[PDB]
Structure formats: structure tokens, C-alpha cells
Image 1 (cartoon, rainbow, N blue to C red):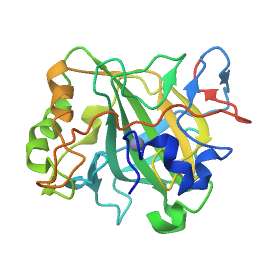
Image 2: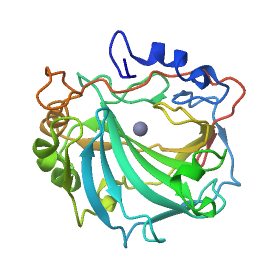
Image 3: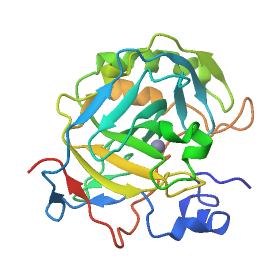
Image 4: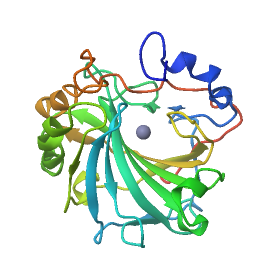
Length: 258
Ligand SMILES: [Zn+2]
């Protein structure tokens, strides 16, 4: 009876095994664009992904992760609300069974078709496992996906998904360039929050970009063909792997832009 996204193990159950689910700095949240405060003290984000080394793609039974080599400062995020250098370790997505839902973060209650998370950890803690125990240990870049035109830079990801259909499968995935997933503008909202899957630790500085990227109906259809289950256990399509919005409680969302 492991956690997941179904009727009987889904987000409304998670608190029984992970009491921090009802904590004071849980994610995701709804971003109220009229209540977000412009903070002109926020620096622009610095994304240096020109030396990124992707290694592998895998289906971990709740999403697919593309993993990067994080043994040196090769793909890093700096600037913005962050002190220090945060290394990219993996990215993944959350998506829906239909185009009108899928994202974790919402903007004035609007859901997008999917949400990309680029996960980075604070190099001062030395590894990822130590970073998740600290309040400033991780920085996640969140990017919304809407359905429209195809994103060429995602097609390489879509094409290998057939080879990792079921839980526990992996495949070599070298020379993928994550710069092909970024929108044009780097304006962002930021707030302190949590992992959105168990263990839901409150170690994340969230940076959510204002500008969505567009993907095609056909691209996102291919995400929906993946499986939560292992080979060949009964087929359960990996859809709606998103956590609903949580109470903002005592936090302020800040914007880098007016
Ligand atoms: Zn995520």
C-alpha cells in the first residue's frame, strides 16, 4: 500500500505516512497574481546549462526523470532569490488525463496541461541527500506547458518514452540539452515551499516562470501512454500525477516583474 495518485493512496491520504503533508510550507500553491509582491531587489536568474551532461531516463512509477551528472558544477542555477550555486540533478513532469489539468501550480486558479520541474541542489551541502534536510537545500524551476505548437526540443524525450513504459525501466539518455525546454523570458514568481511528492520535505525555494512553453497535443498524448505499474502487472495509465494546491498560510509570493 505505497503512496500514489489513486482513490485509495492519493494525495489526500499522504499525511497518514508523512505528517508534514499538513505542514506550514507545503507545495504547490495557487499563485494570485494580484496579491504577489514585486520585489525589485530580486536579481535576474542565471541559468548556465551549456555544459549539462544528461545520463539516463527512467520511469520511477510516479513520473519519468531525466538525470544529469551532478559530480561537478556543469549545469547550474544561480541568482534570483538564491544565495550560492545549485546544481541540476534531474527534471521531470506532472501531467493530466485531459488538457485542462495537469499542472501543480496554478495561476489565478488556471491549470495548465503539464508542469516541468528542473530540480537543483545547493552545492554547499555536498550531496542531494544532505541538501533535502535543509530549508535552502533545493531550488526547483517550474515551467508550465500549454497545448498548441510543438516544442522541437522536447521531441527527443517523447521518442524514448516507449522504451521506459513501465515502472523501473531505464534507458541511456545522453547529449540532451535542457536549454531547448526554456521559455523566452525568465521572469518568475518565487516562494518557499516543499517537495510535491513524499517525503514532502520543506527544503525548496520555488522559482516558477511566468511564461509557459507550448507543446503539441501529440507530444502530451505520448506522456499519457506511460504506466504507473511494472511489467506486466495490470495496466494503469500514468496520468494525473499532480498534487492539488495547498494552503499558502503565512507566506508571501514575490514577483521579479511588475
Ligand atoms: Zn515535480
